[PDB]
Length: 350
Ligand SMILES: [Ca+2]
Ligand SMILES: [Ca+2]
Image 1 (cartoon, protein in one colour):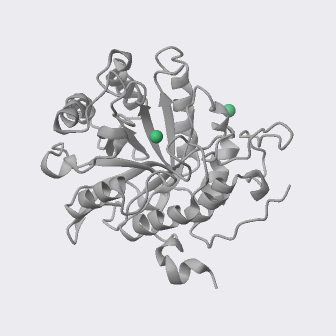
Image 2 (tube, rainbow, N blue to C red):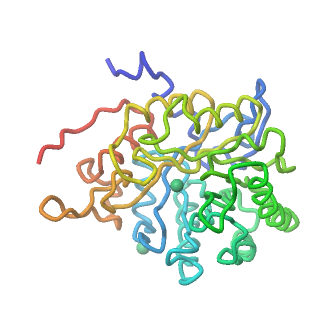
């Protein structure tokens, strides 16, 4: 009866969504022309999980009961910790680092991989002055958690043209590499064998630059970010992704949402079914935006809306689960897809 069984069969199941306790240290392997993430034994793995929103704004999700719910009730094997730099983030309020550290420890404690995301966004060039602390930040995390097999580093969320920015061309890609290579080098010199994920121009829509001009490191993957109200299967972003995957580039969806790219609108679930069917079929890991109760469709939790609803609390109790009615439409859908169960939405009639 579930509609996905006939139409989108790779949406059902989770046998490859292995936790650290089972998978151990990750690697990239070559399999039938593709470079894909695999576990310690060389068996394909898929990471599926959730991103925080900016930790300067929504740190409340960094609590053990929420992390346990995500790992156990939602079936996540990854969580992404989005540390803005600008916009009230680390450049002006460095105490957000403390929340990233806490989050790494809670991911480990709850048997998940963890992505540490230096969340470049405004402005768009990772080399900009505001981001000068990036190399020392990664240094510090690696000193605290040396060669830790749970951690994946994401050096620059979304290179993009916001001034001062990067261009959507080969010159823009060169600025990204010039940024990333010295950090990678430092991490490797320090003995860190972690997977490192590298963004690309146009808001991490251009993993295809790695076809002819990859970074020379066998544990680097390339991000692609999409939002299903904006970006459609067989559209620009999708085809750049597909072109990279086909050509053997290792690709990881570190951020996607069910809204427009603004974080709002919809959600657009029928389009999400098409993207996730492709990602699951092609062994591409994915992380959904975001673990917030802000009033925007991409947030996973019900928001405060005057006259309508109190916010769902991100600081969860000892039951280690949110009721489905406490999840937004997006969060309920994403939970279903992480777990690999049929999507069977609740009625929402106020
Ligand atoms: Ca807390
Ligand atoms: Ca984004």
